[PDB]
Image (cartoon, grey):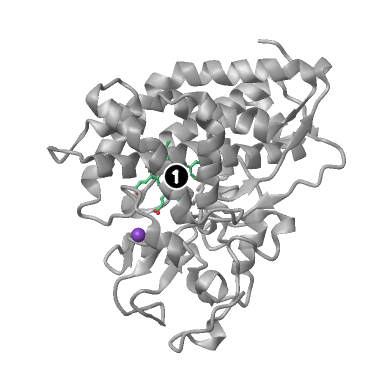
Protein backbone atom coordinates (compact mmCIF):
# COMPACT_ATOMS: atom_id res chain seq x y z
CA UNK A 1 0.00 0.00 0.00
CA UNK A 2 1.41 3.30 -1.28
CA UNK A 3 0.99 6.71 0.24
CA UNK A 4 0.30 9.49 -2.28
CA UNK A 5 3.55 11.19 -3.29
CA UNK A 6 4.00 14.59 -1.59
CA UNK A 7 4.18 17.57 -3.96
CA UNK A 8 7.79 18.34 -2.95
CA UNK A 9 9.16 14.91 -3.81
CA UNK A 10 10.30 14.50 -7.38
CA UNK A 11 8.73 11.64 -9.28
CA UNK A 12 12.06 10.45 -10.70
CA UNK A 13 13.37 9.69 -7.19
CA UNK A 14 10.52 7.29 -6.33
CA UNK A 15 11.60 3.71 -5.54
CA UNK A 16 8.94 1.87 -3.56
CA UNK A 17 11.07 -0.21 -1.22
CA UNK A 18 9.26 -1.89 1.71
CA UNK A 19 11.63 -2.23 4.68
CA UNK A 20 9.27 -4.73 6.44
CA UNK A 21 8.72 -6.90 3.34
CA UNK A 22 11.34 -6.18 0.66
CA UNK A 23 10.81 -7.61 -2.82
CA UNK A 24 13.89 -9.62 -3.14
CA UNK A 25 13.71 -11.19 0.40
CA UNK A 26 13.88 -14.79 -0.81
CA UNK A 27 17.49 -14.12 -1.98
CA UNK A 28 18.57 -13.14 1.52
CA UNK A 29 17.80 -10.00 3.45
CA UNK A 30 21.18 -8.16 2.88
CA UNK A 31 20.69 -9.06 -0.82
CA UNK A 32 17.18 -7.65 -0.81
CA UNK A 33 18.36 -4.34 0.67
CA UNK A 34 21.36 -4.24 -1.70
CA UNK A 35 18.90 -3.75 -4.60
CA UNK A 36 18.99 -0.09 -3.46
CA UNK A 37 22.61 -0.02 -4.67
CA UNK A 38 21.98 -1.34 -8.26
CA UNK A 39 23.26 0.84 -11.16
CA UNK A 40 20.46 3.20 -11.93
CA UNK A 41 19.31 3.86 -8.34
CA UNK A 42 20.15 7.33 -7.00
CA UNK A 43 21.98 8.03 -3.72
CA UNK A 44 18.75 9.27 -2.10
CA UNK A 45 15.31 7.87 -3.05
CA UNK A 46 11.73 8.20 -1.77
CA UNK A 47 9.56 5.18 -1.08
CA UNK A 48 5.78 5.46 -0.86
CA UNK A 49 5.60 2.41 1.36
CA UNK A 50 5.07 2.53 5.11
CA UNK A 51 3.58 6.04 4.99
CA UNK A 52 6.32 7.42 2.69
CA UNK A 53 9.89 8.36 3.54
CA UNK A 54 13.36 8.97 2.17
CA UNK A 55 16.11 6.32 2.05
CA UNK A 56 19.81 7.07 1.77
CA UNK A 57 21.35 4.25 -0.18
CA UNK A 58 25.10 4.88 0.05
CA UNK A 59 27.57 4.95 2.96
CA UNK A 60 28.72 8.51 2.18
CA UNK A 61 25.20 9.94 2.74
CA UNK A 62 24.36 7.58 5.61
CA UNK A 63 27.50 8.68 7.48
CA UNK A 64 26.96 12.35 6.74
CA UNK A 65 23.34 12.36 7.97
CA UNK A 66 24.28 10.48 11.17
CA UNK A 67 26.92 13.14 11.88
CA UNK A 68 24.53 16.08 11.28
CA UNK A 69 22.12 15.96 14.26
CA UNK A 70 21.11 19.60 13.64
CA UNK A 71 19.24 18.69 10.47
CA UNK A 72 18.68 14.94 11.13
CA UNK A 73 17.10 14.44 14.55
CA UNK A 74 16.70 11.19 16.47
CA UNK A 75 13.42 12.36 18.10
CA UNK A 76 11.46 10.21 15.62
CA UNK A 77 13.87 7.48 14.57
CA UNK A 78 11.60 4.62 13.39
CA UNK A 79 9.39 4.17 10.38
CA UNK A 80 6.40 4.16 10.21
CA UNK A 81 5.70 7.61 11.62
CA UNK A 82 3.39 6.35 14.43
CA UNK A 83 6.20 4.10 15.66
CA UNK A 84 8.75 6.91 15.48
CA UNK A 85 6.45 9.30 17.28
CA UNK A 86 5.75 6.81 20.05
CA UNK A 87 9.43 5.91 20.35
CA UNK A 88 10.94 7.52 23.47
CA UNK A 89 13.71 5.18 24.52
CA UNK A 90 16.75 6.90 26.07
CA UNK A 91 19.33 7.74 24.86
CA UNK A 92 18.23 7.06 21.29
CA UNK A 93 15.25 9.48 21.17
CA UNK A 94 17.51 12.38 22.26
CA UNK A 95 19.96 14.51 20.30
CA UNK A 96 23.06 16.17 21.73
CA UNK A 97 23.60 17.98 23.88
CA UNK A 98 21.19 16.46 26.43
CA UNK A 99 21.62 12.95 25.06
CA UNK A 100 25.15 12.60 26.38
CA UNK A 101 24.58 12.47 30.16
CA UNK A 102 22.33 9.50 29.63
CA UNK A 103 24.90 7.61 27.51
CA UNK A 104 27.36 7.87 30.27
CA UNK A 105 25.03 6.23 32.67
CA UNK A 106 24.15 3.46 30.17
CA UNK A 107 27.89 2.77 29.95
CA UNK A 108 28.07 1.77 33.63
CA UNK A 109 25.89 -1.13 32.77
CA UNK A 110 27.07 -2.33 29.40
CA UNK A 111 30.52 -0.73 28.99
CA UNK A 112 33.85 -2.49 28.46
CA UNK A 113 34.54 -2.79 32.23
CA UNK A 114 31.25 -4.66 32.75
CA UNK A 115 31.85 -6.95 29.78
CA UNK A 116 35.33 -7.85 31.06
CA UNK A 117 33.62 -8.91 34.30
CA UNK A 118 30.98 -11.01 32.49
CA UNK A 119 33.64 -12.77 30.40
CA UNK A 120 33.75 -15.91 32.53
CA UNK A 121 29.98 -16.42 32.66
CA UNK A 122 29.63 -15.73 28.93
CA UNK A 123 32.20 -18.44 28.28
CA UNK A 124 30.57 -20.87 30.67
CA UNK A 125 27.11 -20.48 29.13
CA UNK A 126 28.39 -20.84 25.56
CA UNK A 127 30.24 -24.02 26.54
CA UNK A 128 27.31 -25.52 28.43
CA UNK A 129 24.83 -25.00 25.57
CA UNK A 130 27.25 -26.31 22.90
CA UNK A 131 28.37 -29.34 24.89
CA UNK A 132 24.74 -30.35 25.45
CA UNK A 133 24.00 -30.01 21.71
CA UNK A 134 27.20 -31.73 20.56
CA UNK A 135 26.06 -35.39 20.81
CA UNK A 136 22.56 -34.84 19.40
CA UNK A 137 23.86 -34.23 15.83
CA UNK A 138 21.24 -31.53 15.20
CA UNK A 139 19.66 -28.37 16.49
CA UNK A 140 17.22 -25.57 15.72
CA UNK A 141 19.93 -22.96 15.97
CA UNK A 142 17.62 -19.96 16.49
CA UNK A 143 15.82 -21.53 19.44
CA UNK A 144 18.63 -23.72 20.83
CA UNK A 145 21.49 -21.19 20.88
CA UNK A 146 21.02 -17.83 19.15
CA UNK A 147 18.14 -16.85 21.48
CA UNK A 148 19.20 -18.46 24.81
CA UNK A 149 22.87 -17.55 24.80
CA UNK A 150 22.69 -13.73 24.53
CA UNK A 151 19.24 -13.44 26.17
CA UNK A 152 20.26 -15.43 29.28
CA UNK A 153 23.32 -13.22 29.57
CA UNK A 154 21.19 -10.07 29.38
CA UNK A 155 18.66 -11.42 31.90
CA UNK A 156 21.56 -12.28 34.26
CA UNK A 157 22.97 -8.73 33.83
CA UNK A 158 19.46 -7.24 34.46
CA UNK A 159 18.59 -9.65 37.33
CA UNK A 160 15.36 -10.72 35.60
CA UNK A 161 13.96 -14.24 35.72
CA UNK A 162 14.49 -16.39 32.63
CA UNK A 163 10.89 -17.52 32.60
CA UNK A 164 9.93 -13.96 31.62
CA UNK A 165 11.82 -14.32 28.33
CA UNK A 166 8.97 -15.48 26.12
CA UNK A 167 6.79 -12.52 26.93
CA UNK A 168 9.62 -9.92 26.73
CA UNK A 169 10.91 -11.45 23.46
CA UNK A 170 7.46 -11.28 21.94
CA UNK A 171 7.18 -7.56 22.87
CA UNK A 172 10.68 -6.67 21.63
CA UNK A 173 9.94 -8.40 18.31
CA UNK A 174 6.75 -6.38 17.78
CA UNK A 175 8.88 -3.21 17.94
CA UNK A 176 11.34 -4.30 15.26
CA UNK A 177 9.47 -6.87 13.04
CA UNK A 178 5.75 -6.53 13.92
CA UNK A 179 3.48 -9.50 13.06
CA UNK A 180 0.50 -7.07 13.14
CA UNK A 181 -0.98 -8.09 16.46
CA UNK A 182 0.53 -5.07 18.26
CA UNK A 183 1.43 -1.53 17.21
CA UNK A 184 4.79 -0.18 18.31
CA UNK A 185 2.99 2.04 20.91
CA UNK A 186 1.15 -1.02 22.35
CA UNK A 187 4.37 -3.11 22.60
CA UNK A 188 6.18 -0.20 24.20
CA UNK A 189 3.32 0.31 26.73
CA UNK A 190 3.54 -3.39 27.59
CA UNK A 191 7.34 -3.37 28.12
CA UNK A 192 6.99 -0.30 30.37
CA UNK A 193 4.15 -2.07 32.26
CA UNK A 194 6.58 -4.89 32.98
CA UNK A 195 9.31 -2.52 34.10
CA UNK A 196 7.43 0.00 36.23
CA UNK A 197 7.11 -2.20 39.37
CA UNK A 198 10.64 -3.64 39.07
CA UNK A 199 12.09 -0.06 38.80
CA UNK A 200 10.15 1.05 41.89
CA UNK A 201 11.27 -2.01 43.87
CA UNK A 202 14.88 -1.51 42.91
CA UNK A 203 14.93 2.19 43.79
CA UNK A 204 13.59 1.27 47.23
CA UNK A 205 15.98 -1.63 47.66
CA UNK A 206 18.99 -1.48 45.27
CA UNK A 207 20.89 -4.53 44.12
CA UNK A 208 23.92 -4.67 41.87
CA UNK A 209 22.03 -5.72 38.65
CA UNK A 210 21.66 -3.36 35.67
CA UNK A 211 18.15 -2.14 36.45
CA UNK A 212 19.25 -1.16 39.98
CA UNK A 213 22.26 0.69 38.59
CA UNK A 214 20.23 2.68 36.08
CA UNK A 215 17.33 3.34 38.37
CA UNK A 216 19.51 4.65 41.23
CA UNK A 217 21.94 6.42 38.84
CA UNK A 218 22.88 10.04 38.35
CA UNK A 219 23.07 12.01 35.15
CA UNK A 220 25.54 14.94 35.01
CA UNK A 221 25.34 14.73 38.81
CA UNK A 222 21.53 14.95 39.35
CA UNK A 223 19.30 11.93 40.17
CA UNK A 224 17.62 10.11 37.28
CA UNK A 225 13.77 10.18 37.37
CA UNK A 226 11.66 6.97 37.47
CA UNK A 227 10.31 7.78 33.99
CA UNK A 228 13.91 8.26 32.63
CA UNK A 229 15.06 5.02 34.19
CA UNK A 230 12.14 3.22 32.51
CA UNK A 231 12.89 4.74 29.11
CA UNK A 232 16.57 3.66 29.46
CA UNK A 233 15.86 0.15 30.83
CA UNK A 234 13.42 -0.47 27.99
CA UNK A 235 16.12 0.23 25.40
CA UNK A 236 18.65 -1.96 27.14
CA UNK A 237 16.06 -4.81 27.07
CA UNK A 238 15.52 -4.32 23.33
CA UNK A 239 19.32 -4.33 22.68
CA UNK A 240 19.69 -7.44 24.84
CA UNK A 241 16.91 -9.44 23.28
CA UNK A 242 16.93 -8.59 19.55
CA UNK A 243 20.40 -7.72 18.18
CA UNK A 244 23.08 -10.37 18.77
CA UNK A 245 20.29 -13.04 18.74
CA UNK A 246 19.64 -12.33 15.08
CA UNK A 247 23.25 -11.67 14.09
CA UNK A 248 24.47 -15.09 15.37
CA UNK A 249 21.94 -16.85 13.08
CA UNK A 250 23.19 -14.96 9.99
CA UNK A 251 26.79 -15.86 10.84
CA UNK A 252 26.14 -19.49 11.56
CA UNK A 253 23.99 -19.87 8.45
CA UNK A 254 27.00 -18.57 6.51
CA UNK A 255 29.49 -20.88 8.27
CA UNK A 256 27.12 -23.85 7.71
CA UNK A 257 27.13 -23.16 3.95
CA UNK A 258 30.94 -22.40 3.75
CA UNK A 259 33.33 -25.21 4.89
CA UNK A 260 36.30 -23.29 3.55
CA UNK A 261 35.52 -20.41 5.84
CA UNK A 262 35.14 -22.67 8.94
CA UNK A 263 38.33 -24.43 7.83
CA UNK A 264 40.16 -21.13 7.82
CA UNK A 265 39.01 -20.52 11.40
CA UNK A 266 39.74 -24.08 12.60
CA UNK A 267 43.25 -23.94 11.07
CA UNK A 268 43.98 -20.32 12.21
CA UNK A 269 41.96 -19.50 15.41
CA UNK A 270 43.80 -16.19 15.80
CA UNK A 271 41.80 -14.96 12.79
CA UNK A 272 38.52 -15.16 14.74
CA UNK A 273 38.31 -11.52 15.86
CA UNK A 274 38.99 -10.29 12.33
CA UNK A 275 36.40 -12.78 11.01
CA UNK A 276 33.91 -11.36 13.60
CA UNK A 277 34.42 -7.89 12.08
CA UNK A 278 34.01 -9.03 8.49
CA UNK A 279 30.83 -10.94 9.35
CA UNK A 280 29.49 -7.81 11.15
CA UNK A 281 30.03 -5.98 7.82
CA UNK A 282 28.59 -8.62 5.51
CA UNK A 283 25.60 -9.64 7.73
CA UNK A 284 24.91 -6.17 9.08
CA UNK A 285 21.26 -6.09 10.10
CA UNK A 286 19.97 -2.80 11.55
CA UNK A 287 18.14 0.05 9.75
CA UNK A 288 16.68 3.01 11.59
CA UNK A 289 16.76 6.74 10.75
CA UNK A 290 15.98 10.33 11.58
CA UNK A 291 13.50 13.15 11.07
CA UNK A 292 14.20 16.48 9.30
CA UNK A 293 14.22 19.38 11.73
CA UNK A 294 13.89 22.00 8.96
CA UNK A 295 13.66 22.26 5.20
CA UNK A 296 17.14 21.39 3.95
CA UNK A 297 18.79 20.72 0.59
CA UNK A 298 20.96 17.57 0.89
CA UNK A 299 22.92 16.20 -2.09
CA UNK A 300 20.77 18.20 -4.52
CA UNK A 301 17.47 17.02 -3.01
CA UNK A 302 14.99 19.29 -1.22
CA UNK A 303 14.05 17.69 2.10
CA UNK A 304 11.11 19.14 4.02
CA UNK A 305 10.77 19.70 7.76
CA UNK A 306 9.15 16.60 9.24
CA UNK A 307 10.11 14.21 6.43
CA UNK A 308 11.47 10.95 7.76
CA UNK A 309 14.69 9.56 6.31
CA UNK A 310 15.76 5.92 6.69
CA UNK A 311 19.56 5.75 7.02
CA UNK A 312 20.23 2.02 6.90
CA UNK A 313 23.27 1.12 8.99
CA UNK A 314 23.25 -2.21 7.09
CA UNK A 315 24.00 -0.55 3.78
CA UNK A 316 27.24 1.40 4.42
CA UNK A 317 29.44 -1.69 4.48
CA UNK A 318 27.58 -3.37 1.61
CA UNK A 319 28.30 -0.27 -0.59
CA UNK A 320 30.91 -1.11 -3.29
CA UNK A 321 32.14 2.52 -2.86
CA UNK A 322 33.27 1.50 0.66
CA UNK A 323 34.34 -2.14 0.08
CA UNK A 324 35.20 -3.80 -3.17
CA UNK A 325 33.27 -7.01 -3.91
CA UNK A 326 31.08 -6.25 -0.89
CA UNK A 327 29.04 -9.44 -1.00
CA UNK A 328 32.21 -11.60 -0.67
CA UNK A 329 33.33 -12.62 2.81
CA UNK A 330 37.07 -12.16 3.09
CA UNK A 331 38.48 -12.65 6.56
CA UNK A 332 41.72 -11.07 5.34
CA UNK A 333 39.99 -7.93 4.05
CA UNK A 334 42.48 -5.09 4.76
CA UNK A 335 40.13 -2.19 5.53
CA UNK A 336 36.70 -3.42 6.75
CA UNK A 337 34.52 -0.34 6.35
CA UNK A 338 31.07 -0.47 7.99
CA UNK A 339 28.48 1.31 10.18
CA UNK A 340 27.02 -1.90 11.66
CA UNK A 341 26.98 -0.43 15.17
CA UNK A 342 25.81 2.94 13.94
CA UNK A 343 27.65 6.22 13.45
CA UNK A 344 27.94 9.61 15.13
CA UNK A 345 26.86 10.39 18.68
CA UNK A 346 24.61 7.34 18.97
CA UNK A 347 27.29 4.71 18.26
CA UNK A 348 26.21 1.44 19.86
CA UNK A 349 26.87 1.18 23.60
CA UNK A 350 26.49 -2.59 23.53
CA UNK A 351 29.09 -3.24 20.84
CA UNK A 352 31.75 -4.52 23.27
CA UNK A 353 29.24 -7.01 24.77
CA UNK A 354 28.10 -7.98 21.23
CA UNK A 355 31.68 -8.61 19.99
CA UNK A 356 32.49 -10.69 23.11
CA UNK A 357 29.36 -12.82 22.54
CA UNK A 358 30.12 -13.34 18.88
CA UNK A 359 33.88 -14.15 19.28
CA UNK A 360 33.11 -16.57 22.16
CA UNK A 361 30.46 -18.28 20.07
CA UNK A 362 32.81 -18.73 17.10
CA UNK A 363 35.72 -20.07 19.21
CA UNK A 364 33.63 -22.37 21.34
CA UNK A 365 31.43 -23.80 18.64
CA UNK A 366 34.24 -24.37 16.15
CA UNK A 367 36.31 -26.20 18.85
CA UNK A 368 33.44 -28.62 19.58
CA UNK A 369 31.45 -28.84 16.35
CA UNK A 370 33.86 -28.00 13.46
CA UNK A 371 31.77 -29.71 10.79
CA UNK A 372 28.04 -28.97 10.36
CA UNK A 373 25.58 -28.04 7.62
CA UNK A 374 22.04 -26.93 7.00
CA UNK A 375 19.41 -29.67 7.40
CA UNK A 376 18.81 -31.14 3.97
CA UNK A 377 15.91 -29.61 2.10
CA UNK A 378 15.60 -26.64 4.49
CA UNK A 379 14.77 -23.42 2.59
CA UNK A 380 16.18 -20.82 5.04
CA UNK A 381 13.90 -17.72 5.18
CA UNK A 382 14.95 -14.28 6.44
CA UNK A 383 12.66 -11.52 7.81
CA UNK A 384 13.21 -7.77 7.52
CA UNK A 385 12.48 -4.71 9.59
CA UNK A 386 14.27 -2.34 11.95
CA UNK A 387 16.45 -5.35 12.87
CA UNK A 388 16.51 -8.18 10.31
CA UNK A 389 16.67 -11.85 11.22
CA UNK A 390 16.54 -15.56 10.30
CA UNK A 391 13.14 -17.39 10.73
CA UNK A 392 14.70 -20.83 11.54
CA UNK A 393 18.07 -22.45 11.12
CA UNK A 394 18.02 -26.24 11.29
CA UNK A 395 21.62 -27.59 11.54
CA UNK A 396 22.83 -31.19 11.44
CA UNK A 397 26.22 -32.80 11.98
CA UNK A 398 27.72 -36.26 12.60
CA UNK A 399 28.41 -36.53 16.31
CA UNK A 400 31.34 -38.75 15.38
CA UNK A 401 33.15 -35.66 14.01
CA UNK A 402 32.69 -33.57 17.17
CA UNK A 403 35.14 -32.85 19.98
CA UNK A 404 34.53 -32.82 23.74
CA UNK A 405 36.66 -30.18 25.49
C1 LIG B 1 25.17 -7.15 16.72
C2 LIG B 1 24.61 -6.55 17.78
C3 LIG B 1 24.24 -5.07 17.78
C4 LIG B 1 24.02 -4.26 16.74
C5 LIG B 1 24.30 -4.46 15.24
C6 LIG B 1 23.63 -2.99 17.28
C7 LIG B 1 23.44 -1.79 16.54
C8 LIG B 1 23.17 -0.53 17.02
C9 LIG B 1 22.95 0.65 16.25
C10 LIG B 1 22.99 0.72 14.69
C11 LIG B 1 22.72 1.66 17.11
C12 LIG B 1 22.49 3.14 16.76
C13 LIG B 1 20.98 3.41 16.50
C14 LIG B 1 20.71 4.87 16.10
O1 LIG B 1 21.67 5.64 15.81
O2 LIG B 1 19.50 5.25 16.04
C15 LIG B 1 22.79 1.14 18.45
C16 LIG B 1 22.62 1.86 19.61
C17 LIG B 1 22.59 1.36 20.86
N1 LIG B 1 22.82 0.05 21.27
FE1 LIG B 1 23.37 -1.48 19.97
N2 LIG B 1 23.60 -3.07 18.69
C18 LIG B 1 23.85 -4.38 18.97
C19 LIG B 1 23.96 -4.83 20.28
C20 LIG B 1 23.57 -4.16 21.43
C21 LIG B 1 23.50 -4.73 22.76
C22 LIG B 1 23.76 -6.23 23.03
C23 LIG B 1 23.02 -3.78 23.60
C24 LIG B 1 22.71 -3.83 25.12
C25 LIG B 1 22.49 -4.90 25.88
C26 LIG B 1 22.90 -2.54 22.84
C27 LIG B 1 22.58 -1.28 23.33
C28 LIG B 1 22.52 -0.12 22.62
C29 LIG B 1 22.16 1.15 23.18
C30 LIG B 1 21.85 1.44 24.66
C31 LIG B 1 22.19 2.12 22.07
C32 LIG B 1 21.79 3.58 22.09
C33 LIG B 1 23.00 4.50 22.12
C34 LIG B 1 22.50 5.90 21.99
O3 LIG B 1 21.41 6.19 21.40
O4 LIG B 1 23.26 6.83 22.32
N3 LIG B 1 23.30 -2.82 21.56
N4 LIG B 1 23.15 -0.21 18.38
C1 LIG C 1 18.16 0.31 16.36
C2 LIG C 1 18.55 -0.44 17.65
C3 LIG C 1 19.32 -1.70 17.25
C4 LIG C 1 19.33 0.41 18.67
C5 LIG C 1 19.43 -0.53 19.88
C6 LIG C 1 18.03 -1.24 19.90
C7 LIG C 1 17.40 -0.73 18.60
C8 LIG C 1 16.19 -1.53 18.06
C9 LIG C 1 17.11 0.67 18.96
O1 LIG C 1 15.88 1.09 19.27
C10 LIG C 1 18.36 1.51 19.10
K1 LIG D 1 9.28 10.18 19.43
Q: Residues within 10 Å of mark 1 (few under 14, many from 20)?
A: some
Q: Which residue is mark 1?
A: 190
Give the structural element (helix, strand or loop) at label 1: helix
Question: Height in image: 145 above or below 284?
Answer: above
Question: Height in image: 20 above or below 354?
Answer: below
Q: Residue at x 39, y 41 (%)?
A: 193
Q: Position of residue 244 (x, y in %)?
A: 53, 38
* Quarter in which the N terminus is drawn: bottom right
> In this view, which residue lies farthest toward the left?
221
Q: Position of residue 382 (x, y in %)?
A: 68, 50
Q: Which picture quadrant has residue 125?
A: top right
Which quadrant of the frame does ligand 3 lie within?
bottom left
* Quarter in which the C terminus is drawn: top right
In the rendered structure, the answer to whether residue 202 lies left or right of residue 192 reads left
Q: Which picture quadrant has residue 364?
A: top right
Q: Residue at x 22, y 33 (%)?
A: 217
Q: Between residue 133 and residue 165, name the one nearer to us.
A: 165
Residue 168 seen in the figure: yes
> In this view, which residue lies farthest toward the top?
405
Q: Position of residue 330 (x, y in %)?
A: 63, 44
Amino acid sequence: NLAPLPPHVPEHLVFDFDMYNPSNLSAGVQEAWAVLQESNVPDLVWTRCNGGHWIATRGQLIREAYEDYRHFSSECPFIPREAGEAYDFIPTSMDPPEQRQFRALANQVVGMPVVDKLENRIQELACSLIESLRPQGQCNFTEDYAEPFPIRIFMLLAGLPEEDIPHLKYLTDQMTRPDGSMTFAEAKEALYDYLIPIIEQRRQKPGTDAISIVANGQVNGRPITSDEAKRMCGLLLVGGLDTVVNFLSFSMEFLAKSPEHRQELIERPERIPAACEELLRRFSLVADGRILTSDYEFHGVQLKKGDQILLPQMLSGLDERENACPMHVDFSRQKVSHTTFGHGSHLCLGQHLARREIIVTLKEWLTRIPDFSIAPGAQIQHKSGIVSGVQALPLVWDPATTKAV
